[PDB]
Amino acid sequence: MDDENDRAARAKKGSPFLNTAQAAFYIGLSQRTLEKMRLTGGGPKYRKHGRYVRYHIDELDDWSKGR
Amino acid sequence: AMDDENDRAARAKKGSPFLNTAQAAFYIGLSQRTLEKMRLTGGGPKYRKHGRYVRYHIDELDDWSKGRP
Amino acid sequence: MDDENDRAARAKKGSPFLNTAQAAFYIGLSQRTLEKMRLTGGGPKYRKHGRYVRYHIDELDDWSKGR
Amino acid sequence: MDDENDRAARAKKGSPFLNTAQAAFYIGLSQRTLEKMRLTGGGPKYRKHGRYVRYHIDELDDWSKGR
Ligand SMILES: [Cl-]
Ligand SMILES: [Cl-]
Ligand SMILES: [Cl-]
Ligand SMILES: [Cl-]
Image (cartoon, rainbow over all chains, first blue to last red; front, side):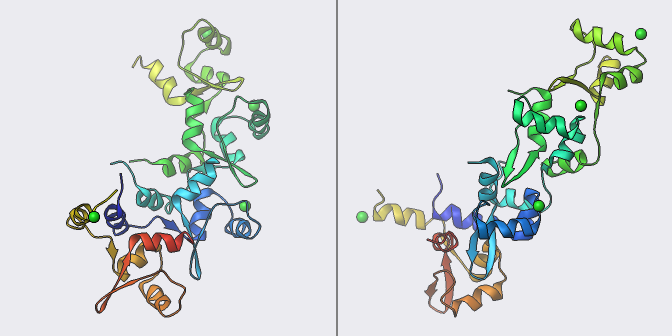
């Protein structure tokens, strides 16, 4: 394989990021449990998109599997 | 046809493939304690640790039921 | 058309599995009869759920219909 | 590795650049939100291609990943 052109072309076709409400529902936790995981750690990697918090679907899945 | 990260994220926004112990036990026809005990004895299905909360992927449940190695 | 989200949602609403007693009553056999068929390597396909034999309703019907 | 011929060959097949609408949708913010951040020094690096703003996908990802 993947170069910058494939990455850009895929990025124009959709998004891999979920918000907190979506990440929590997908992984089967309370939104508040997920938020509290940010502050104490132990939860999945997030991204700070400035103000907003965003979760990359493949980082959710990695965390779930222990990978 | 092979799904990319956009595809996976788009499905994840529409549902969840995970069950808690109580739901997983009901689905497989066992008591919750029996399923919990198998986490100690071994011999039950793969599960995920989502922090301190145990979750079961429905397809890893079906795998275990069907005897996939 | 079903994906992993559909399968989990359905699994959360009930169970397709019968124990030996239920399966026997359903196919019109004694519980003992159904066990011996299993122990002799015959009868319907079943699942080992740990120490507990379980029967999927559709595998029960497949075996009954000889197809 | 790449020589200049390789870079040119790749540039002739695709573009690594997204506009604001595309870049916003990919990182999961509104278009307006992403514009706003151009004034803040919070958001991702951008290129000014004359009058028009463009985001290199790899800089989008570096900013999200916190570099
Ligand atoms: Cl919770
Ligand atoms: Cl039981
Ligand atoms: Cl009989
Ligand atoms: Cl060169």
